[PDB]
Image (cartoon, coloured by chain):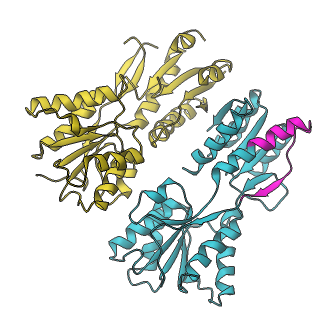
Chain colours: A cyan, B yellow
Amino acid sequence: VIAAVVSNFAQQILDGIQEEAHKNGYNLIIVYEEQKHALLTAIERPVMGILLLSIALTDDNLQLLQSSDVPYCFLSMGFDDDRPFISSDDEDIGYQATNLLINEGHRQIGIAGIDQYPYTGRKRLAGYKKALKEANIAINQEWIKPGDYSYTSGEQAMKAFGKNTDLTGIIAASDMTAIGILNQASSFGIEVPKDLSIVSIDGTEMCKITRPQLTSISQDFFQMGVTGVQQIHQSVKNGSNRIVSQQFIPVNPVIRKSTARL
Amino acid sequence: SNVIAAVVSSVRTNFAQQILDGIQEEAHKNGYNLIIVYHALLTAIERPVMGILLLSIANLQLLQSSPYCFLSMGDDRPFISSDDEDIGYQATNLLINEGHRQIGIAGIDQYPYTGRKRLAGYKKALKEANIAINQEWIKPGDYSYTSGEQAMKAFGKNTDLTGIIAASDMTAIGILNQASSFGIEVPKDLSIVSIDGTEMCKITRPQLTSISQDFFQMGVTGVQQIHQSVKIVSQQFIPVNPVIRKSTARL
């Protein structure tokens, strides 16, 4: 029995876990202080492994999971330390998203909705700034509008940029953030991709339901889930009952209808 | 043990999430712990759990042994859910009360306890409006976005329908996007009433008018029922009501 800890991208990871699990004959329970109790809820009952779907554990909750001697691995999130994880290369996500617009002729490129403090956001933003520097585009703090990856932060950031923004391209922190940017731009009378290109990060089904459909840097969440279960399975096989690997799952741009050459 | 199990298997919408939020809040209020399973029953049974909630699922014999309550699906079985027949009824009447008579319904599954009941509420409204039930106006599906697109393609660019009832918000969006690709303006050329009323209705353009369900309450009341039986035969219907947005207009 494998336990997955969760706080659209999750379902995609869960489907992958569910498949790899039922391929190993494993069972799966999803554990929804809310944190500390989530860990205990999973450990209290006998489980062979724990997968944490983009969960930022506190310092003590982490030592807690590490002391239970239960094989574990984080999914869709990277770390600075040696904690085991499987996710995308966040810096490369920001790098690819930005270059996608640069290669389409854009130079006044903004980025919105990213929670700039944590590891995830820090890396994606660094990738964005690298892409700009390699294109000899001066980093403009006004082109960076932080948020929390939500739909609202997308709407708020677009308001910040303004109806008369000089930006011609914007990278969204997430698909929901991209939809907010998209709708707010629309309210300002800004046509996408006509006078504004938008590149979304994640590439879940949400990208195929907006008009225009969102071009994105898609993460292979499914594979994260598949690999995650393979690390647990491998931890019981080699008898170590422990996971220490950190891996990056490649991402790929999926061109839809929200981008156009400058 | 103080853990409640919630059984939810593959869903094409965000409805479960809505119900879970309710379960969570009412669970925390009692120190309860929540786990979720997608066979599924055994995983929950072999695990000493306080109670089980089945969010729109259809093995109960195995269940009876082991305290359970069905959520979002409605005859001895305990349950908390919307009146699916009334949903179909209200959805259709919202359009009939706006002058529409050529109304279609898409995305509903032809299964007995939920889909059939909505289709029934639909046929009921057409009957009272003395509208001839037309089979070509019913396009079965699985409540998904894709089912919405395909059902609209089936209705056709040259559809004579002026209003369409979608099985879910996701299906509603599929219908809206496909209609638009056909050059069919909503609500100018076509009215769309969505069922569920989740935030999905707020991020679409035009925003989707809907027959909204109180999924949250269903989750809260599910936990309340668990906390009571251990301190279940109850059958409760959580009311639904329309929320007018920008996807409908008088004929």
Q: Is residue B163 visible?
A: yes
State yes or no: residue A80 in magenta: no
**In the rendered image, the vertical position of residue A156 relative to residue B158, given as above or below:** below
Q: Is residue A123 visible?
A: no
Q: Closer to the camera, A139 or A95?
A: A95
Q: Residue at x 84, y 40 (%)?
A: A234
The part of the image, by quadrant, that contains residue B138 is: top left
Q: Residue A140 in the image: x percent, y percent?
A: 59, 85
The part of the image, by quadrant, that contains residue B181 is: bottom left
In the rendered view, does A144 fall on the left or right side of B247?
right
Residue found at the very far right of the displayed protein:
A239
State yes or no: residue A234 in magenta: yes
Q: Residue at x 42, y 57 (%)?
A: A209
**In the rendered image, the vertical position of residue A176 relative to residue B3, given as above or below:** below
Instruction: Give the residues drawn in magenta, as a range.
Output: A229-249
Q: Closer to the camera, A58 or B243?
A: B243
Q: Residue A204 in the image: x percent, y percent?
A: 54, 55
Q: Residue A72 in the image: x percent, y percent?
A: 79, 43
**In the rendered image, the vertical position of residue B163 relative to residue B53, given as above or below:** below
Q: Which quadrant of the rendered structure holds the N terminus of chain A?
A: top right
Q: Residue at x 50, y 25 (%)?
A: B54
Residue found at the very far left of the displayed protein:
B130
Q: Residue A8 in the image: x percent, y percent?
A: 54, 49
